[PDB]
Image (spheres, rainbow, N blue to C red):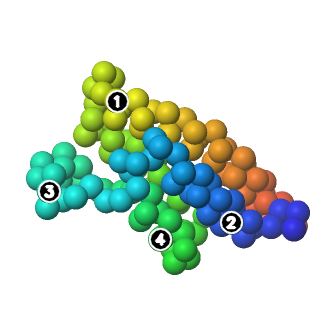
Amino acid sequence: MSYDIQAWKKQCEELLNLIFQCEDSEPFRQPVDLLEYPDYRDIIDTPMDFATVRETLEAGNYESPMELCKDVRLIFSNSKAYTPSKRSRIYSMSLRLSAFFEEHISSVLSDYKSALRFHKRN
């Protein structure tokens, strides 16, 4: 179990469970409704949402926690592009949940890279 290179998957499932519980995740749980928000695709090239991230992890389509972290960061960078105004309550929600995610993902990434370095050396 020390330096287990697969432990990040369960850690990421647990973190996504916390994120889905957070009231701040409500706008980001499901894809933006493309048929009902007509100008969304005029602004955003690559939509992303937490249900898509959770399904990608479950399907085994992330090779590392860094790939999962890239998709989650796209959720927040898309929100900042579409809702850029610091006055907006949606801007505030995105910033709070981004900080929460970045705090909790830190140890998952550091542990995973430590494990990589250990198995590569040995």
What residue did someone put label 3 on?
A: 36
Location of residue 95 (image quadrant): top left
Disc 1 crowd, CA 10 A, few/some/many (<14, 14-19, 20+): few
Question: Which one is earlier in the sequence, the residue at label 3 or at label 2?
Answer: 2
Q: Secondary structure at mark 4?
A: helix
What residue did someone put label 4 on?
A: 55
Please state the horizontal and vertical placement of residue 58, each as a whole percent of the image.
55, 74
- Circles 1 and 3: CB distance less than 8 Å? no
Residue in view at x 19 percent, y 45 percent: 43
* Alpha carbons under labels 4 and 2: distance apart: 13 Å
In this image, 73 relative to 33: left or right?
A: right
Q: Amino acid at mark 3?
A: Glu
Asked if 68 appears above or below 63 in the picture, the reply is above
* Alpha carbons under labels 4 and 1: distance apart: 28 Å
What residue did someone put label 1 on?
A: 89
Q: Secondary structure at mark 3?
A: loop
- Circles 1 and 2: CB distance less than 8 Å? no
Residue in view at x 12 percent, y 48 percent: 39
**Residue 10, label in figure:** 2
Residue in view at x 67 percent, y 51 percent: 109
* Foreground disc of the pair 1, 2: 1
Question: Which one is earlier in the sequence, the residue at label 4 or at label 3?
Answer: 3
* Foreground disc of the pair 4, 3: 3
Q: Amino acid at mark 4?
A: Glu
Question: Which one is earlier in the sequence, the residue at label 1 or at label 3?
Answer: 3
Question: Which one is earlier in the sequence, the residue at label 1 or at label 2?
Answer: 2
Question: Which one is earlier in the sequence, the residue at label 4 or at label 2?
Answer: 2
Q: Secondary structure at mark 2?
A: helix
Asked if 54 appears above or below 99 in the picture, the reply is below
Disc 3 crowd, CA 10 A, few/some/many (<14, 14-19, 20+): few
* Alpha carbons under labels 4 and 3: distance apart: 23 Å
